[PDB]
Structure formats: C-alpha cells, structure tokens
Image (cartoon, rainbow, N blue to C red; front, side, top):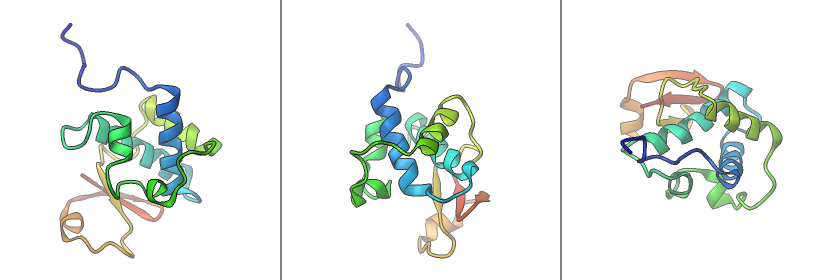
Length: 128
C-alpha cells in the first residue's frame, strides 16, 4: 500500500502496440528523437492529473492522436515506432516533460502558441 496506484502498473503488450501506432501516426518520417518525443508525451499525459490515467484514455481522447481518426490503430505496429515507445517507457523523455506539441507552420491555437516553448524536434514544437 501507499504506492503509485493512480497510474498503470507497467504497460501491457496491447498498451505498447496501441502507443506505437499512435506514435507512427504523429511522427512517421521524423528523426528518431521526434518519435521518442511523441511516445514520451503520451506517457506524460498518462502520468499527468490533466489527462486520463490509462493509455487508452489518453490515446482515444478526441483529436489527440491522428491515427485514431485516420483508422490506423488495429494494425501491426511500425518497428521503429515501437522501439521509440520502449525507449520512452524506459525513461527517455527528450521533451522536458511536455504535454502538448504542434506544428508552427499550421497551429492556430492561441493557448498553445502562448505556452513557453520547451523545444523543437523536427516539425514539432513541444510545450507544457
């Protein structure tokens, strides 16, 4: 008792495969660091009080991950996306505890644009 019981007790094989497919939908063709970056943001959302506390809850939150609306969820995961998920699970967060990201070329959200930018990796600026 008294442990970290508000977050998942590790991640299942389903959780990993789901997250890999989410990562791929966000970061195909990006530098590897940017793939780890999206995986880290997923985990940061899971562990944040501001978002759902299950992998499913985070991935399926409306508009959160393009792979859901695009219909690229129930399929065999990309190898390097999955490796990025495992790297993030093992504690690599290149984003400085980011919860959000955007593409500066396209983003229209005042709120997102007004958060301190942590950093840019590839096409994504990361924020919290």
